[PDB]
Length: 32
Length: 32
Image (cartoon, rainbow over all chains, first blue to last red; front, side, top):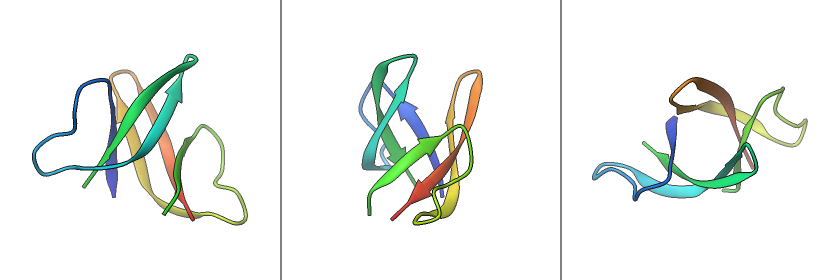
């Protein structure tokens, strides 16, 4: 898989698969 | 599965399942 750490909702083909924390801040983990 | 984006190796109890990407950074995607 390749996932993207996003602050906005996941892309249309992505699934929310968890969270990332980067510089203290949570991001959506969006995977395909 | 519970997945984490890691700067180092995946935990012994996790599997390398891909990468996590944001602008400027790459991480291992590590899943259980």
